[PDB]
Image 1: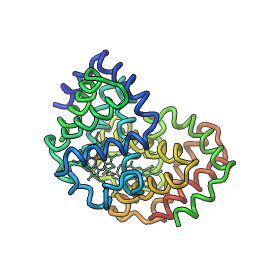
Image 2 (image 1 turned 180 degrees about the vertical axis):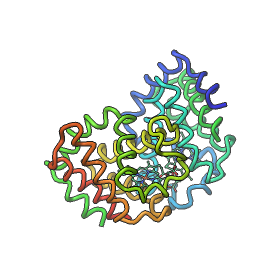
Image 3 (image 1 turned 120 degrees about the horizontal axis):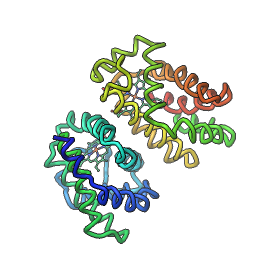
Length: 145
Length: 145
Ligand code: HEM
Ligand code: HEM
């Protein structure tokens, strides 16, 4: 149930998501690439999914990876903006899942993003509390996969 | 070239884009659905492309349509935010075009969105001058299709 998962986003969780997002969301290009490069470093077994992006080890220098990384941050921007209305949050998460489902990305696969997020947050001085909050948002997406 | 197209975005054009976007982009759910509904109303032939969305005549009530309309607006949010750096605008546009090319959407088909955009702008009192500005942004994407 995606709705039950969204119900886990309590007042405190939503507050922490916004506070952290105010910082990491201000530099979508920088933090977006950092998130992807950390994913490829910690989970090399996922690189096979981004073969269209060429040599992802190039990081910021790869124009295809940079385009994907920036675009990725706008999906998160969308989720944060829908935190007030769970009905809209759910419909945008299901729309989001469509393409990832077509790519055969399973919930187990997607959950691997939690590590990179925790590390990116940490580099910006955000601790456990914030990593946990984001883990709850990702859970909503997983329930839709 | 997508890069050459991005050159049409002069200072005055980028100004009208941001000014108009501050308004139509302030209500993504509302205007986003207006864009889609207007598209289906004036260009019935495009309804076949969105069969996944189910019954698009339901408008706001259709969760799938609402989810798509809100997500669509964040693609435009992305373009607007990259206006000052042609390099970033280009890579995000090419990324964006990937899925639309796989769906067989030609540059001419995509251009059909100009009509709906014009009307949505007009509903907020933004005249031909702004419509033309947006037509140039859409042209950038067309250069990649
Ligand atoms: C917070 C996590 C994530 C976000 C916000 C995110 C966001 C996005 C967005 C916005 C797109 C572009 C639109 C589309 O094609 O659907 C996309 C594409 C893609 N995503 Fe996700 N994604 C995330 C995690 C993942 C993970 C963990 C995988 C795989 C293990 C994955 C694999 C893909 C692939 C392969 C593409 C296509 C890239 C390309 O060819 O350009 N995504 N994702
Ligand atoms: C202002 C122009 C437009 C924007 C910003 C836009 C944005 C988007 C976005 C963000 C997606 C979701 C990610 C993905 O590509 O899978 C999408 C999907 C799609 N777009 Fe575009 N689009 C635009 C115009 C059009 C037009 C004119 C057509 C065709 C007449 C079109 C056909 C499609 C289709 C068929 C989908 C998949 C919908 C589904 O089955 O869920 N788009 N578009």
